[PDB]
Amino acid sequence: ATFEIVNRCSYTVWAAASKGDAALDAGGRQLNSGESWTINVEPGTNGGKIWARTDCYFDDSGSGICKTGDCGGLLRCKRFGRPPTTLAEFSLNQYGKDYIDISNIKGFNVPMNFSPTTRGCRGVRCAADIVGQCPAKLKAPGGGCNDACTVFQTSEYCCTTGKCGPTEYSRFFKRLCPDAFSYVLDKPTTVTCPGSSNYRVTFCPTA
């Protein structure tokens, strides 16, 4: 399957793509404002994620640091990034279907639209100003808005016992972005698409 990753933000973003234990395609790339990066994701990929990283510095060897979404200091991510990260999530070719969603479960850093480029399903979008409105306790110094599990590490926010309810914090994300997961047991906002669809992830879709 092919993914076009488009940076419509006015600032440089460092895109990342990983399935947790391995990079997808090259795994990461600088995208200046307006730049598009097309990657090939192998069919059958389970648990793939795409996110943006902000305020990165990397050297010759591709080592450095980002203030949001750092994946252990690498330009080409092999593992997942450090929150806060708005997450585009996908499982491909699962019994003939594709499943996509946007998640705020690891916080929010960049607004995002996640849409298919082929037929038969809708896209999803979280493009509200979550950082500007972020509750004080969740504001991350490096920018972005942390999820409550990252900040407080309780069984309720992290849903450790498998039983948990919505919270004042999860409701904040859900009220600004109803189409994104706000906590781990949220009523699923997953979208079902035909198997082997193609997609576009746009950062800053509106502004």
Image (tube, rainbow, N blue to C red):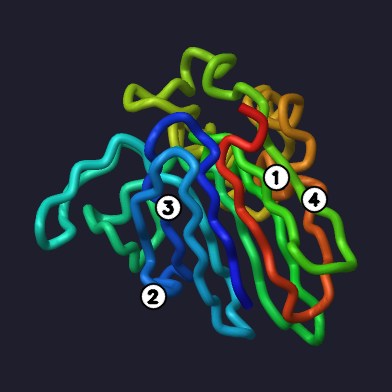
* Depth check, front residue: 197 or 70: 197
Q: Which mark is residue 15?
A: 3
Disc 1/disc 2 C-alpha distance (Å): 24 Å
Disc number placed over residue 189 in the picture, else none: 4
Q: Is residue 60 left or right of residue 122?
A: left
> Which residue is under mark 2?
22
Tell us which disc is closer to us: 3 or 2.
3
Query: Tag 1: Cα neighbours inside 10 Å, few (<14), some, or many (≥20)?
Result: many
Q: CA distance from mark 4 to mark 2?
A: 26 Å
For the residues bearing labels 4 and 3, Cβ distance under 8 angstroms: no
User: Which amino acid is tagged 4?
Assistant: Thr
Mark 4 or 2, nearer chain start: 2
Q: Which of the marked residues, 3 or 2, is nearer the chain's N terminus?
A: 3
Look at label 3 and name its amino acid: Ala
Residue extending farthest to the right is: 120
Q: Which percent across, then down, holds residue 97?
A: 80, 78
Q: Are marks 1 and 2 in contact (CB under 8 Å)?
A: no
Is 195 located above or below residue 163 in the figure?
below
The Cα–Cα distance between marks 3 and 1, rounded to whole angstroms, is 21 Å
Tell me, for residue 32, which label it has, or none: none
Q: Quadrant of the N terminus?
A: bottom right
Q: Quadrant of residue 112?
A: top right
Specify the label residue 181 is tagged with.
1
Label 2: element kind: loop
Whether label 4 touches label 2, CB < 8 Å: no
